[PDB]
Image (tube, coloured by chain):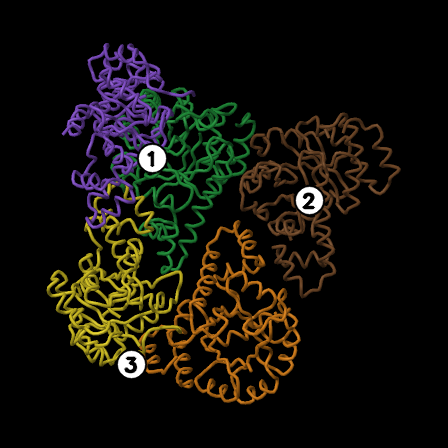
Chain colours: A orange, B brown, C green, D purple, E yellow
Amino acid sequence: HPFSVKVGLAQVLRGGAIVEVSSVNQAKLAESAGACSVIVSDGVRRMPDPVLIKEVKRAVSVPVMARARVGHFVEAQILESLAVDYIDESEIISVADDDHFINKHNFRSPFICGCRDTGEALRRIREGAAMIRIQGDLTATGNIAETVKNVRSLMGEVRVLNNMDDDEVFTFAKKISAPYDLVAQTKQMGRVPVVQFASGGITTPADAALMMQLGCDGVFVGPDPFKKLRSIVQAVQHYNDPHVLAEMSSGLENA
Amino acid sequence: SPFSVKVGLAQMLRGGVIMDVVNAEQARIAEEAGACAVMALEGGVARMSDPQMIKEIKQAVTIPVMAKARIGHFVEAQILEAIGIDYIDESEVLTLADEDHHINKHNFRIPFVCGCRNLGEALRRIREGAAMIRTKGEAGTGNIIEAVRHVRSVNGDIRVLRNMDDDEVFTFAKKLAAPYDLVMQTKQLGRLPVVQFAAGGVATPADAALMMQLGCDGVFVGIFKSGDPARRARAIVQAVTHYSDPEMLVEVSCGLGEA
Amino acid sequence: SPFSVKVGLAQMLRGGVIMDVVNAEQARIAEEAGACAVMALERVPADIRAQGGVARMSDPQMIKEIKQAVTIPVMAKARIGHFVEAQILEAIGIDYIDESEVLTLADEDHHINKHNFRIPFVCGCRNLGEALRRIREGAAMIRTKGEAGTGNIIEAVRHVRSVNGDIRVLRNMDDDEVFTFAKKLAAPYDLVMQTKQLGRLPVVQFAAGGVATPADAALMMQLGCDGVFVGIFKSGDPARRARAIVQAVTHYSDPEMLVEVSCGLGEAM
Amino acid sequence: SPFSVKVGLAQMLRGGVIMDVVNAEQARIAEEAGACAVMALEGGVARMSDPQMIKEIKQAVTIPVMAKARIGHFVEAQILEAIGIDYIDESEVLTLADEDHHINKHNFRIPFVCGCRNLGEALRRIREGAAMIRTKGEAGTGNIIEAVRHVRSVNGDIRVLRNMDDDEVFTFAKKLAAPYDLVMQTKQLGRLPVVQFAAGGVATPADAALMMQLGCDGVFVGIFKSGDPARRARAIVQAVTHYSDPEMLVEVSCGLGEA
Amino acid sequence: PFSVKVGLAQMLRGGVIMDVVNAEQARIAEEAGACAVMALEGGVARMSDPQMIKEIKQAVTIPVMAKARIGHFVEAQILEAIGIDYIDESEVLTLADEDHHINKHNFRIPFVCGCRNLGEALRRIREGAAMIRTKGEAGTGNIIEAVRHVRSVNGDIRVLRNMDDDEVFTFAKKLAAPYDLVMQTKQLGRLPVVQFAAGGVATPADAALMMQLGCDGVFVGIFKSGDPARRARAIVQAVTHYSDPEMLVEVSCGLGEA
């Protein structure tokens, strides 16, 4: 399926960190530190200027993502035209449609969408999201609390579903306002049918490793960047190695 | 597919009238008046009827025999299926056995009828396996006002769905809290994916014809509560067959007696 | 432990139908129909509800008589918290004591300390926390109760699904989250983990409340219970009915048999 | 001290059962069944009983005779004291005569029994002169649930008080709204400074033994409301004396009749 | 292994644990007689930089503690791999998991956990806390809340000690605490682990008051004063001689601005 293909594309990002960058300079640093991809961003917050996105794409060889406003299917048409690798329909910038998200099945470019619980995730996937970011705080709070909450909520509901009496799954789907067939699939896989990255408030190597130990596939990250970024990449790569995590965190500078 | 077949079985009831019966006598009077199928049943807790009386009814008439099971009472269903009933009515007019879950109807070979009050609820019942939808108003009042409300509700939303922008159907599915697949499938067909009858309050020929004129594939009647049941039954049956023929509707409603 | 033994003693009841009785004749009709045990009391729950007054432990006399009429185990109800009604039942030589919430609550804040007894206890519950608390108090057997003396099985279904639902949630739960789960349940952490590992209640679990027909009883078994209570004599023909329910529990996964035993059973309550 | 003496008088009732009586007959049946003392009394306003019937009862039995006075009705008390009653029960089961004040019991030579629902209330009654406390549950229901609540309440707080930090007892006294002297005196003794019985709902031998096992020095019974009063009375009396003997409790509860 | 961690904590009884944000202080703290130091360094507050933790673990000879955000089991994994003696899962740092605390049994090093009442203490212990600190207000210099919580815990413990055994089941429910630990606590007549006081302990009098209430020691966050070295020693002496008013007068005498 074309969806299976998109879901297959995002799967190459597993085990990685995605870094938000605002220039060719930041993009280059992020690549050097081993970021699996960069997500381009430039009051109302909108899709970034295509010129900036082009410069970033040329400056690096890792996949390039860019944001579109929720429900702004034209911005998404534009991003797909200039040939980005992924589009993030991102609640971090200003929502353009309060009631409807982008009909992501109409695009060839794979989409990431945010979520705070299992029902949300599945709704985004039914709309055609190939990847999900389980999101905490929207601002740069450097606080991972809400992210942990929403990762545990998603992971926890999946575990409840896994073992659930089959007869009760219909009502369960209703309660979380999710498409039944996707709930059924998630039950079978004992996992959400797409790549799932933690995002929001990730500030330290310990934060990033925590997300991985909670079961995520990777993380998004928003006075020494090169070092900090390398530390987080290493953290995600060796999230089960406390000795490595220790080295990574040593004198990283002010977070 | 097994489900598609069950759906097909229920289509042989279109344009028909289903009548409640409590004895073999009534069942014959019902078949004699031209009922498409009969529904076997007998305050106080209301449960599935005794298989004894069900067997007697299935042995008196040659038309399809249906029977009620309490909502969520999957074992009652199993028992009805094992005695060779043609249809099972997981009906809310019986005493609810399970408050949060309905019977998983797919796990059965016999087709199910479920009730509903709106589109979302109809689609949820269908996703659970229901092969035939009963849009129910008020039970045991003889007042069709609620049935009209629900029929208009379901058919109203179906028409809204037909012409809706495809990018808005996802949100619509959420608002209905219904399975997206079935919502789109309903959008395509431009109608309910299964047979749809009306039930509740139908007390006169005019009531029955009104349901058909609204869009219902048929009606349930709960008759012998009238003055001359045999007469009233035939009138309603004719009403359903000739629902767009006033001259006829006048002819069968004339001197019907106490309704 | 002496608690391990009491728990064992109850295992013999798995697959059984316990019946309420108000005299000998009935107790005999209950065993004659194949009841795994009888529960002696001077009023059935339906009559308790319809009548009122204060429902207490039954007079020993009527308990001794019943216990001499049948060979299957004999149970008796003791008001919740009334540890002296219990002592009296223990002394009388009954098999099990049901600290029953269908009788008139005697202590609003504290259940009987059941460990202080050598005789096994059955306690009612409505959810998992309530069951694990009763067990920690000593209860060797648990019956998840719906509504009593109505003939409506809906609340029993709610509670069964409630207890079994959380048990399944508990089994697959992240180990680090069980502590919080125990708090929310308001149940002892030890028993919660013992329930997690085992994948079920660490004691025998029966259904009770509104079980009127064979289909009802079989439903409880298919939901995952170990047996049912019936509070049968408020129906048309007790014997035929009692036998049918017993058979239903033994053949709960057999619709053909269920149809057989349900046919012409008479008028239910 | 006069109070200490009154307290001493009430200690000769320990381990006993007090029975309500309305005629000389009942009083004898009560004494015959081994009652420690008898309580004389006869909708509608409930007042002190006629001295005539009280005199007849005090002349039929050789055990102590008690009588009720309405709460706050100090003149009723005076009248009971003047006719040589052994104990006065300022009882809430009679129609309250004064809503804000109780009888000043010190002003009497006869010992008083007062009711209570918690420790603070018991201590307030004692400070007013009460020589014996009745922890009362529900009156005239045959349901002991409320008595259990109150007994556990009083005894619960007494145990909390026993081990409490001395610097926190002042605040505790305030929360109870009870006299500090008596609170400390209760702390020391580790129990109530006066005799404590249970009352309300006691309908069976088991009920009575339960009260004793909880900590009560005895019980009141309100018997003739049973099938065979003489039998039920003796059973309860034996229950109180052998409250920790199940074998006996079974022996006296057997074939007791309608309770 | 849990009973071993508990024992490792009982060592600290009668001691003063002092906060520190660098080596100098850690020494100024050990030189005053602290039984251990607590390493740290608006805005999110997290675990401290290992480097600074190593600089302190190698600058003193008394046990070295460190804070880990509540629920942040990886911050703890890092602290453990650093080789410090105690981990304090502390609510003064920015809460990391609002719903669950760290599973502390999954660690070798002993854990300190804060609490405000007996149920809260017993839950932390069941999660594997080897030591409990009853916390009042943090960084206010006011001990009112600490007094409240100390009296709260010690109060219910005394209630539990003499309680009717039959009623304990319901008591455990109301506390929302594990029955086993409740009955344990009832048998011991105290917390089954070391219990310190923390929050608003500014003066020597405060420290002695906590001991007289029945605490095993105190935390201090001394450095917010006009003369640290003097203040630290006084507080240490106060905890050691918490019954000697004549002594408490000396150590409180001209200690500068608090």
Within 10 Å of disc 2 (Cα), the crowding (few <14, some 14-19, many 20+) is many
- Expressed as whole percent of the image width and height from the top left, the position of residue C177 reads 38, 59
Can marks 3 and 1 be said to lie on one chain?
Answer: no
| Nearer the camera: disc 2 or disc 1 | 1
Residue plotted at (59% across, 45% down): B108
Q: CA distance from mark 2 to mark 3?
A: 71 Å
Q: Dot 3: what SS?
A: helix
Residue on which the image places disc 3: E51
Q: Which chain's residue wears label 1?
A: C
x and y percent of residue D106 in the render? Answer: 22, 28
Query: Image point 74% across, 55% down: which residue?
Result: B159
Relative to C98, say whether A54 is above or below: below
Q: Position of residue D34 (x, y in %)?
A: 22, 17
Amino acid of disc 2: Thr
* Residue under pointer 1: C107
In the rendered view, would you say C46 is above or below C10? above
**Chain of the residue that carries numbered disc 3 in the rendered image:** E
User: Can you name the residue that lies furthest to the right here?
Assistant: B247
Q: Which mark is residue B135?
A: 2
